[PDB]
Image (cartoon, rainbow over all chains, first blue to last red; front, side, top):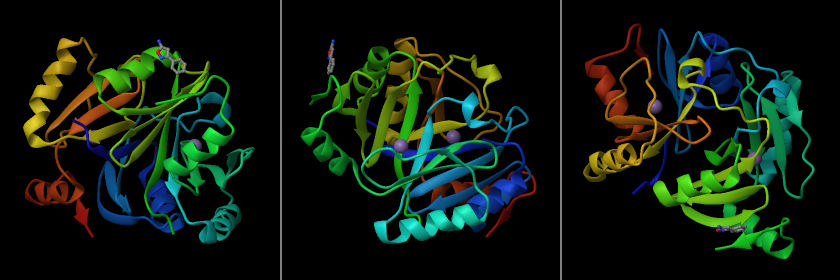
Length: 137
Length: 137
Ligand SMILES: Nc1cc(-c2ccccc2)no1
Ligand SMILES: [Mn+2]
Ligand SMILES: [Mn+2]
């Protein structure tokens, strides 16, 4: 039986700018680096950056909705989003829902998100105002 | 400050086969389903499946190394891997070894992995046989 996410690996086109983004801009802990990768952590999350000649810097119009959201508190949300704006980090979507989300791109065009709130909170909001066709189990 | 992964969203081309894969075959818990998505959990992981007509199915040889690994115990690893092979789940190949892992594809070509072991165990293994150019912090 599966017990959770073990690690998330992102393919990157250039290691140095990606390590700078995840370690210095986003504040993740760098544990190890080698000629073709790095291991970082963010709380419980193990993140691997893998240098991949097949990775292209992908504009958000050319990739699908697959994305990775990181947890942050409401109190820290606005200042963290302002930090990203100062560094010139691109936004790929406006938040059009209730709840706090900021949608931003990494150097290779991986789609990231800052989100406040848990699955339980989302389910409770959906029970009050369900999506079309929604069934609960 | 970022505190970990809030959720993982995968774009899928057909909702029903994806829900069946993650719930029936992988054993994740299905919380809700609606006309264009579903919410599942796997331990602490909140997984969202999002119906996206822009999702293409690409051979693993022409997609990059971005992939998602799920935790499984030593006692369950081999029997779970054998169940996936018996169900006809397709495999893919990574360019390097990272310990006890089984690599498989979801119905849309997302690259998945079963892995035994934590980040701390991986760093200890790497100290004894480092990748090229490895530095530890
Ligand atoms: N065959 C089948 C359909 C469904 C369903 C569940 C929730 C929402 C819409 C459809 N569950 O099983
Ligand atoms: Mn999201
Ligand atoms: Mn892996």
